[PDB]
Image (cartoon, each protein chain N blue to C red):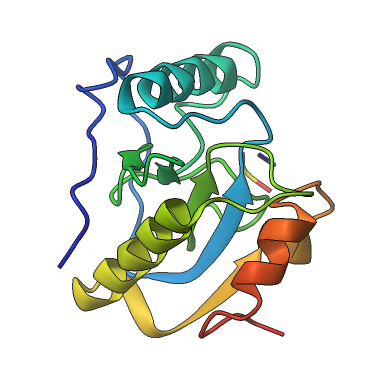
Length: 5
Length: 165
């Protein structure tokens, strides 16, 4: 997994 | 029609109040958990439960980052569901439904039951209006620098309709 961005 | 779908209550998900996902999503991003796999439903729930707590407790996400997960048991597990923001891909958490195959698939691909369940799921999303008809399908690695969903799995989805080449 990568939240926000 | 739509595959069964095992809900959060079934795998005893912790309670949260996270931001809503605005439907319909424009993309579908394929991911693998890169962890252990599971071929029986009770084993998969435990795996999902631990992921939620890993994401929440160590990655500090609001909840499990996936919208749904798929097991080698041919089961579709509810992550945060269709209505909640995701925490799976930078810049696409509000516009992309993140679907993770439970397991590690660089050398070996998910079994037929898993691959099949994943597709029935995608089909359902369109039919139900959760996904735009012209949606784009992409591999986690096409979007961001990350080791997902794994080459073996990548080769399979790249032959899928809507896969963005």
